[PDB]
Image (cartoon, rainbow, N blue to C red; front, side, top):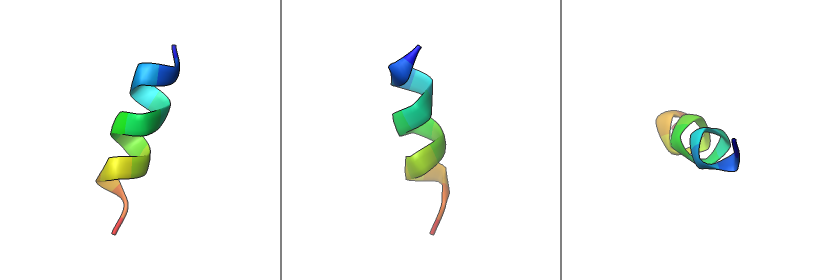
Amino acid sequence: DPQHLRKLLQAAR
């Protein structure tokens, strides 16, 4: 589930 890896990466500032 790489889609969520990206989502969480996108979550970090």
